[PDB]
Structures are given as C-alpha cells and as structure tokens.
Image 1 (cartoon, rainbow over the protein chains, first blue to last red):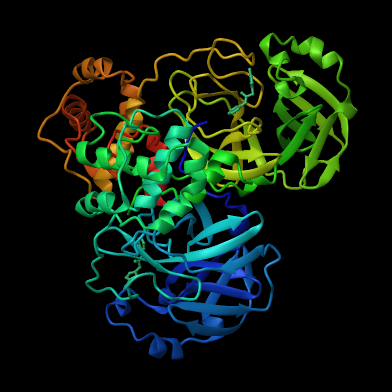
Image 2: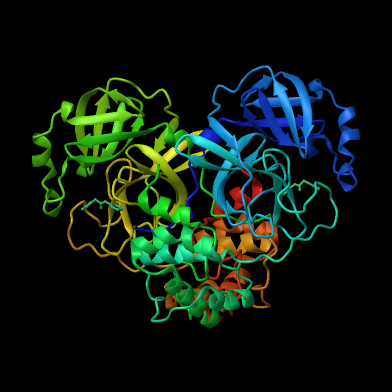
Length: 304
Length: 304
Ligand SMILES: O=C(Cc1ccc(Cl)s1)Nc1cccnc1
Ligand SMILES: O=C(Cc1ccc(Cl)s1)Nc1cccnc1
C-alpha cells in the first residue's frame, strides 16, 4: 500500500543523453542509433529567438559546427537535417546503449516521465502529464532543453516529448520526437499565452480509486449521478467532460473496488461542491489529476 | 522555473538490482561488488514472521538455498552471513555495473530516492523523506522488500535505505545498508505502531523559498518572528522545533531571495494559524515537507 507520483526508471534514457553545442548555445540531445535529436533552437543566439528564420539560420551551419559529446567522448557528425522543430544530427557511431524505442505523440491527459538534463548529464527524474491546454508543469532551467519525456512498456521506451521552451507564465512547451509542437506553441520568443488549464477528470477518478484501494475512503458517499448530471458540475469547475470511453477505461478500477464509476463521479461531485474541509486524500489537500487509470493499475499491481 | 518532487536518475541503482529467492520467498537484493544485500526475512515463511528466531532459521540454510538471479543469469553464492537485519550473500562474480558507492545512515528529515522493485526488476522511482518518527510514506507492495533508497553526489551513490516492512497503518519501515532499522521497528509480524508524524519545519521553509524563487509570493507578509516565538506555534501544530542550525542551513536560500529566515518563519506561522484559504503554493494545497534546503538549491541550480 501507499501511493506515490512514481516515475519510470530512467536508466534506459540516461544512456541516450548527449550534449549538443552550436556556437555558444549548449543543450541536450537524444542519441538513438546513429542519430542525435535536439531542439532546432540550438542554432539560435538569444537575439535570434525574437524573429528566427530557421531555414536561413540553418544554411550558415555545417556538420562540423554541431559539437556532440557523449559523456566525455566526441561524436563525429556526418549529416544534419531539420524535421519540423527538431534537428537530426547523423553521427558515425550508433549508440551502443540504444534501447528498444518508439516515437509516440501522446494525447492530453496522458502522463509520462521526464529525465531533466543539463550539458547532456541527467540531474533528476519526475512524473508529468500533458495538460489539456498542451503545456506541461515541469521543472526546467536554462540548459534543460533537449530533456525528454517517455513511457516504458517492459523494455521498450516510447519517447513522447522533448523540452523546448518556458512560456512567460512559467509553464513548459515542447514537441514530440518528430519536432511537432504539442499545442499551438512556436519556438519564438514572442507573446504565447496558454489556454485554460482544465482538470483531467478521468485521472482524478482513477486517483480516487487508488485512494479507496489504500484505505482513504472518507469521501465515499451514499449518492450516485449520471454522465450528463456529473458533467454539468464538471463544466462549472473547469473539469474535462467525462465520456463513456473514460468510464470504460475506469472499468478495471471499478471492478477491483466494487464501486461503480458513476458512484465515484457522485463522490467527486460532492468534493467539487464542498471541498475537502481540511482533510487529505492520499496525503494531498487537492484533487490530483496526474495519474491515468493505467498508472493506478500499474502502481497498484507492480508492473516491472 | 517550476518545482517538482524530483528523484535522482535511477540508472546506477538499476544495475545493482537482483532477485533473491529462498524457498518460496522472493524479494529484491542489492548487488555491489561480489556481495548481494537483501532483507534477512527472505528465509521466513508467512507463519515464521510471527515469532522469528533468525539465528535458528539461518542454521537450516546453506549457500545453495539462496537463489540469486541478475536479469536472467544465475549468480553462484560462495558464502552467507547475517549482519543485523540484512543478509550478505557473497557471490563469485563482482557486479560489472557497480558504481562508486557508500553506505550512509541518514537522519530523519533527510530525503532520498527509492527505486521500487519486484523480482529484482525496477518498476518505478520516487522521492521520499525519512519521517521524524522513522517511517517512510512510500509505495511498496508484496515483493518490494529489498528495494533501496539512495542519494547521488555526481557519480557516487549513497545507499541509505532498504525496504523491509509495511506496518498495519500502511506506513513503511526499513533499515540502513548495515541492517539496522531506522526507528524502533523490528522485522516481526507483531503490534508495531509508529509515533507522531511531525512536520519537518526546515523542509517547509526551504519549499517556501523555492515557491518565492518561482513566483508564488502571495504568502509573504509584513511580519517577522523570533526562534522561540515561531517554535511556540510550531509546537502547537506538531512541527519540529527549528534550531539555529536549521537557520544556518537555510542561509544560502535566504541570501538568494533576500528574505531573512525569521521573516519566512513569520510567513509560515501565518500559514499555520490561518490556512491557505483555498490557495495553492507550488500547486500544492498543503505545506510540503519533503524537500530539504539542499534539494531546493540543487533543483533550482541544476546539479547534475
Ligand atoms: O525557453 C528557453 C530557451 C528559449 C528562449 C526563447 C525561446 Cl522561443 S526558447 N529555455 C528554457 C529555460 C527554462 C526552462 N525551460 C526552457
Ligand atoms: O511487510 C512485508 C513482509 C512482512 C510481513 C511481516 C513482516 Cl514482520 S515483514 N511486505 C510488504 C508488503 C507491502 C509493502 N511493504 C512491505
């Protein structure tokens, strides 16, 4: 028993972290096979970031201008190309530590681990969620760009995110491993404001199931609700509308605890309308939305 | 910017996780050099745990009874000994992935990362703190015993904890890497109740500094306090007494923000007496006590 914001073991991803220097800019790269992936703003100076023309800026860069360093050895760059907002630096040596991997573009609400890096060296690992407004609430500093988000299925790593930028509101924006930004963000130093940060309803419900499985049951009540009734209350509190699909995904959690999904929605509805009244659920004084139904089942069953 | 409960990269520790089977009991072991460390209750059956005599139970066990498996290869056990509540299984092969390591016994209030394992395979990583009552609030299931807690200083791993047991209150108890339990716990299936879980005051103050550094300043007030005044309020709310030593340790955080430590104590005093009034600090609706002053400086400066 016990519930923690648990990240995937980062070992497989540490072996892929390299340092990419272009001029005076140093950031992190992801070395998989003979390719090093990094954010394309490595070729920019602070001033360039105001109105960058990446195709133009790229012309002035050659293979020998990108300094790729793995640990303390230098990698030879034999080719470079821009795919969307990521640069792909083809090196002559394939990464001996390349795990089985996939590049996946996640949906908002989905969660993943982040291995925060600086100078290609990992410094920490935390569990994040892709917010419904396509931002992430991470912990990134200058030099952290190129740090990646990932999921693991036994031995295969699914890379889903690369960090690119901090918006003026302190939230984070990045791309998938094909260079496409999540959301409407662009790699420019301009006025970019995120949309409403709604709460991931299916994730709070999963975490309420996780609490019940661990002994925290005070929030369980005698009431039930319907999808349309619950959603009228979810709308008012900036909670994502709950669909029959989310209900189905909570099925295994509903089965293990014997609490029908609509009964847990009615509990969540009361928590929304009345607050926690100074109480805690899983040691948290607010409704946690960064555990998916899959994460609860995984943590509660011990998937290695 | 941004503040996350960030764990150390687990790669160096994953390379040390092995599976230890003794009879029908399988748990996790820590393979450093030619020694495998595991909880001594590997030699017990569920029934034995009521009143175990480990020296007696150990006599009936030989080198060939301990099955040590690293990944999928079997390790040959050429010696075994009991040091306090841990077994040390000497194997013939030194772990090629042995990082630079130390065995340290941490103080309560100190924080560390946990690589939760099952069948010697890592499943997740989270950041914990050794509570003042010598328990930890982790996420451990059956099969998790032998999972370790650690800190990293650049490339050296300081192993500080091994998981041994879940108390009936769902909290966790374990030993340092010499087999000595933290707190008054014993590896018996008997009535063991933990003491008061007090809040780590110096850690909340550090996290208030971390919030100020990230833009969350609403809790800053016009007041100050003294160590004795603040402590009268800390006593009432089950907060650890703050010493001049804790004040000195917050010195670098006080210097970076320009907020005197006693001014932050007065802010904390108001938060204790009046609550958050529905507000959040660093996205948390309660006062977080699992970041030490060292962790704040590390996360906020990017120590790799
Ligand atoms: O945002 C940048 C670099 C950029 C400046 C202007 C851009 Cl457009 S991208 N670094 C950063 C710093 C702290 C946390 N996350 C990211
Ligand atoms: O506590 C035990 C095994 C023991 C039974 C009686 C003892 Cl004394 S030690 N496993 C466990 C399960 C879930 C989480 N943490 C630990």
